[PDB]
Length: 219
Image 1 (cartoon, helix red, strand yellow):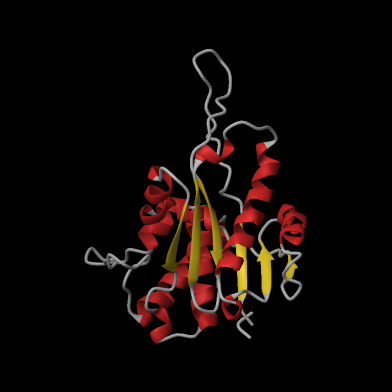
Image 2 (cartoon, rainbow, N blue to C red; image 1 turned 30 degrees about the vertical axis):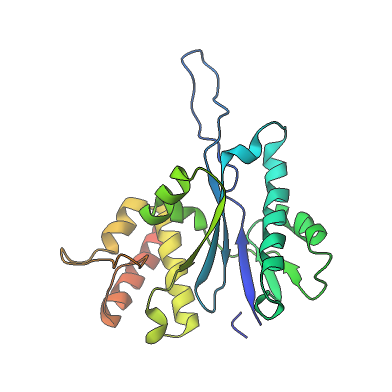
């Protein structure tokens, strides 16, 4: 990482069907809005492609179709960017994305596509209010830009920032309530309106990061 433009692509949250049993005793099939997370680990840039439920109108094997829709949307984003902003490598968090991406990116022979064993659970972002409500309440597809490193890169490297983010996401994923406590060390801890994460000192982040690691280790 950190050397060529690299994107992580997570399709885990694209096709979302909540588990519920009706009064008649059957599983519901109604989806809710999802999203594709497309993330540059050097700069912190997130492209959030919100996927509105209308796109599923009609067809079957929607789990499988969603991998293709993800590939389509990644290709559309690439085509909308100047060549110098296009990724050289795409790393997919799930192996089901490899073939659909390969087929959708035949016009981009320069782009290397690979899988990964890295635990990078963007699904945890659905528990962060900024993202969760935006996704839920959308009435049409759209793309939203974010900076997942807030102002961190003013004082730390991309490597330190990436590690910090991964710890935050994994901790939120494994134990949301406890992670949120760890990330609010004081009553006065705040998150700026345009930031994703709390404003903490360097020293406070060291302590937070140790705690997040311990939480992940525990479960």
